[PDB]
Image (tube, rainbow over all chains, first blue to last red; front, side):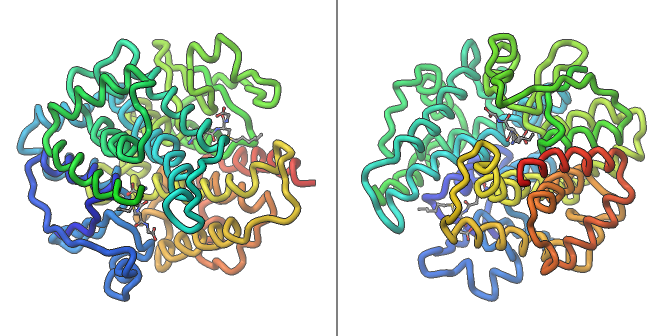
Length: 216
Length: 217
Ligand SMILES: CCCCCCSC[C@H](NC(=O)CC[C@H]([NH3+])C(=O)O)C(=O)NCC(=O)O
Ligand SMILES: CCCCCCSC[C@H](NC(=O)CC[C@H]([NH3+])C(=O)O)C(=O)NCC(=O)O
């Protein structure tokens, strides 16, 4: 399976942790966005949305959006270990609803506001001073996550990390390298330390996050 | 089942269409966001993210994010009709991945870029002259959708509308009612017309969108 990725990219790292958890190797294909490699006719034919991560399965199926890829990996390549797939992606509709909820929270709120705050600080204008509105917004997202983790081990509940934890771990590892003091959010910091110690490929998440950290 | 919502809200309308498809009757609870009804202590207890739509099910289980609600409606409350659930939310991992991919596209790209430009105008934060980047962003998003719909009846493929169609139907209705010219996107217009003609609860999508349209008089 061809995996078009960048080590520094959070959504790429979330798929990497998921693939390691289900036990499938990825054919790593580094796609330099700065050299416009995502804009070459070869990549565009595969992915008109020209974004990473992009997964190309051996049957020719092309898939993007990291969280769609996460679910796909569990559903297709996790069947060999029912209990594992169940831990990562519980089949009970109510339990799965919270997992889905947190996945959408990650893309639309937690990672989104992170990007809306730090991308102006490292690209284009490169302003070191962060907009007070964008900071308030991003902190509100951390406030939300902290509340979700109140009296809970993991982001969508349960006794084991789910793919929602893997997605948000990639995201929050990026928060850490960006210089944000996560210790302000005691539940988040506790969860971040817990999850990093136990999930497969977590060391490769910290490793890739540091590559993103070169921008600051 | 309690449904905290506003008719003008696209994500709310996507849930309404999904519930109509699986025969779920929602107890509609108008949540006036301008009056701060979503910031009231009782609502915050249910939903600390203080956002609509919010579903409270028969056991008091609380769920928000429209697309997670959509899935929950099909998986749990659509399971009485195996064939219908399969049309709305196919179980094949590849087909389901495209549905998921399109749902994420809607939240993170299509609706996201819409809201960034148009939603300020609801709150009164409308700037008469703005950044060209915000306009290019919506154009680009609509180009992607039009490309996905090339040679295809529906947004995630297949012979029937999925929850991805209902999500994007609610979003595109909002584009149209806000005044966006969709004519350069022939596949989008064609898909919108044909999908709106056949999906249950489509009337309330149009009606609800019109309520949103009253902000752009
Ligand atoms: C050091 C690493 C720097 C990269 C960090 C940004 S991730 C790159 C970006 N990808 C995305 O934002 C995809 C997000 C998508 N929601 C997902 O989760 O997969 C991209 O391909 N953007 C280019 C494009 O969309 O055209
Ligand atoms: C009458 C039409 C007025 C326009 C309403 C826009 S939707 C309102 C908004 N909700 C959302 O954007 C939720 C989006 C979420 N991604 C979903 O799909 O459910 C909200 O509750 N915002 C309040 C908040 O989050 O605090």
